[PDB]
Length: 195
Length: 195
Ligand SMILES: [Cl-]
Ligand SMILES: [Cl-]
Ligand SMILES: [Cl-]
Ligand SMILES: [Cl-]
Figure: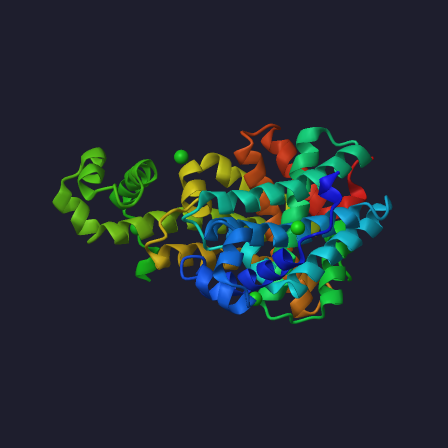
């Protein structure tokens, strides 16, 4: 099947450059001329790969979303020892936001409100993570769907909030401490906070 | 002291009417003429109490914020048995969002972005709840300030997220079940979800 054929190496390089420009300028100020300039490709070659600035922006957003979502899903498939996969998944999330700073900004601090499809892509990806957690909670607990879904939302939201606090506070503790603190709270709740 | 003198009964009635109009119309479409009309007061009497539509909007927002924030603080002073005050506080929050629907919309679904002071009033009130939780976690645990603050953000955020999910899903379970589910997850974490 053609979906297994080698990835377009030039496409990947163009997305990295486009991500730099979109994050630096914002969507409206960013231009295909600057992206072509910085990619070292002619503007017609850039247009052969991406017929519009919007298609390129959505491709950049998707590359960052897929990086995070695949990392979270892969974490959840490592083990069915829930305490352990909770750490692998929270770790994957902190690893993403620390490593892929442009991705963090594009997903969690998106200001391109003029295009509803951008906010929708963020919601559908967020819902993919909540759905993955909901599927595990439903399967591994006696909670009925309504209760499992509320806890899945609480768990994902609590995780996002701890991480955003840590990153927005300029990393006041190590990433390993921030991940472990978030995991211990998610697993044991207030009842297991050190006394 | 003059701060203990009786409340202005007409002021309170005007705020209830103003809240109806602001929620129904949005800030920009709302007018002092409609508020005066519905309050059964003359427009000069309305202006004797509130010199501008913005002052009236901020007074409406504050009345709703104070309702929630005082309810949360009072819940936290009822008992130092943390498992119990966690329920009293989460209950106070669900009671507010269910009873004070206009307050829920004005605080959690605010669309008046043209006035930065509106978003700031919501943030400073949110921070008052996080600060109250942080003060308890710091005092009742061995967590240092950075770790206590991250957990306080996670706890408040998780609570807001469970409640917003419940309300946005048209209350698929009873408020008592939604409160208890949120409290049990906050207290015991994933480790104590029914098996
Ligand atoms: Cl490709
Ligand atoms: Cl960046
Ligand atoms: Cl008064
Ligand atoms: Cl309402």
